[PDB]
Image: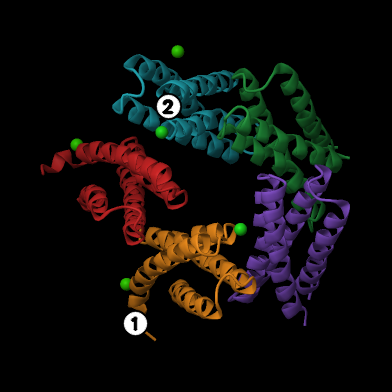
Chain colours: A red, B cyan, C green, D purple, E orange
Amino acid sequence: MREDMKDNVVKDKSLEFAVRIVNLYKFLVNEQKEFVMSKQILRSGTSIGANIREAEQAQSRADFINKLNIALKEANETEYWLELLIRTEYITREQYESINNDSTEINKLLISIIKT
Amino acid sequence: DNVVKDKSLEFAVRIVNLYKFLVNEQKEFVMSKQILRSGTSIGANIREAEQAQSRADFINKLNIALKEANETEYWLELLIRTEYITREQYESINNDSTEINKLLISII
Amino acid sequence: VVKDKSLEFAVRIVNLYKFLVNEQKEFVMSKQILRSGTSIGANIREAEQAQSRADFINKLNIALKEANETEYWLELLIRTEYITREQYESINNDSTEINKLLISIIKT
Amino acid sequence: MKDNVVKDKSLEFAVRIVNLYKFLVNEQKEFVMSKQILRSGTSIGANIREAEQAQSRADFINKLNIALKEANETEYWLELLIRTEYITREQYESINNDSTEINKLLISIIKT
Amino acid sequence: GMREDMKDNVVKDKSLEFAVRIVNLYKFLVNEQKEFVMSKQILRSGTSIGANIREAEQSRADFINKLNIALKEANETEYWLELLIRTEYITREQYESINNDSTEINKLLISIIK
Ligand SMILES: [Ca+2]
Ligand SMILES: [Ca+2]
Ligand SMILES: [Ca+2]
Ligand SMILES: [Cl-]
Ligand SMILES: [Cl-]
């Protein structure tokens, strides 16, 4: 993808992802009656976009990169919770692959920006 | 200082009213609770700032208020993208949030 | 004196929490005030066990901070009709009594 | 022997606290003070365990001080529970006796 | 011992596997033993360990802080295991197996931190 766009695209992807994470939370709580892992991943999964939003408001490029690094942290924690959820049969392989692929797409873009 | 005190409490009230709409009418229970916390915590941190015993503490709490404001703005973006609120609701609340941000930044 | 008042106050906050959750279906501000309101007495107890005057005063200042936070939530709760004016004034009078007694210990 | 004694006593007290939690939730339908004392009451032993695994003296004393804080917090919730009549005077004295026994052991060790 | 530079890689892997075991212990406790208190607590502490280890992947200070949180949660988990064996909700076999896995994580974290 065009290098200039990477930040604008990762913002939009993170908002779409937050919405998917909200839906996953509802699924886990309402259908699977799972209250512990669900709360953890609701937080980490929606915090990716929140930190990207802080990054966009940075007063320095330093602060920008740092906020993106916190977004990356949150993406990685979310990936941990997703892996735990598939291994313990709270989500199907289809659910896992779909959501995890969106997560890892965000990882890739954040790393590019950070490393760019 | 008095002004952002009043405005942040008034803003907390509006967030509660938005929360009531979301739970009672839209039957939305996840994002509503998130914005309820972040949006009412802005005034909580401002009040803590008012009572601070040092300048660093004062600025530190006002910075936390600004972080809660940005979180609140984030949840509002998600609520309009997902069509749980109207553009009118979004603009009205965001106008009030912007006013508080400007005040905090001026003070900080 | 303030010790006993803070324990009685913690009981009122526990019962307010139960009212907010079970009757008003409110889970977020209720959680905040449960914490702040019961933390007052917990910190006053910690104060009594402090090994220095500085640590004694620090713990009482934290209790005072928690009292102030409590009062913010109470104000928001009456403004948003989760509690009556009568409930607010009763509970707030008790909370602010604790501010006064703490300040007298710390500063006089 | 205070080290081994406070370990044993804190584990027994933790079990008492789990049983108090069950009583409060199942019989008394009390979900708020119960949750708080479950945390504090079991945190005493948890912190004693961390103290035992401490790599330094500062870490050791820190963790025992946290245990003592958690013992004092447990006694605070116990006071709230007797005040609201969720436990009897006898129940209160019995559980409080065990908590204060731990307080004294912890202080003794910290002051060594 | 293993190479120092592999301890972080291994503790990451082991903590995920351990979180899986803890979830399975939770399911056993609630479904088979009808135990609802310690099970919920250990679920939280035991799954949190690997989450904090993942976070440490993203300052030396902050790195050490996160790993110390993971270590605290490992110890909390090990305390709940102690309570579970003391109260006879798990066998000595289950206790030793799960505890050994948990304490292998403690050892790796301590070494990485020091
Ligand atoms: Ca761009
Ligand atoms: Ca306006
Ligand atoms: Ca490595
Ligand atoms: Cl919902
Ligand atoms: Cl049970």
* Residue C31 or residue B49, whichever sits in front: C31
Element marked by disc 1: loop
Q: Which quadrant of the rendered structure holds the N terminus of chain D? A: bottom right
- Measured from the top left, where is residue C49 in percent x and y? 80, 56
Q: Which quadrant of the rendered structure holds the C terminus of chain D? A: bottom right
Q: Chain of mark 2?
A: B
* Residue E105 or residue A83, whichever sits in front: A83
Going by the numbered disc 2, the residue's amino acid type is: Lys
Q: Is residue E110 left or right of residue B94?
A: right
Q: Residue furthest bottom?
A: E1
Q: Is residue C72 left or right of residue E75?
A: right
Residue B27's label in the rendered image is 2
In the displayed structure, B24 sits above or below D82; it is above
Callout 2: CB less than 8 Å from ligand 4: yes
Residue B49's label in the rendered image is none
Do circles 1 and 2 both sit on a common chain? Answer: no
- Measured from the top left, where is residue D6 in percent x and y? 74, 74
Residue B53 seen by the camera: no
Quadrant of the image occupied by residue E105: bottom left
For disc 1, the marked residue is: E3
In the displayed structure, B68 sits above or below D34; it is above
- Measured from the top left, where is residue A85 in percent x and y? 35, 56
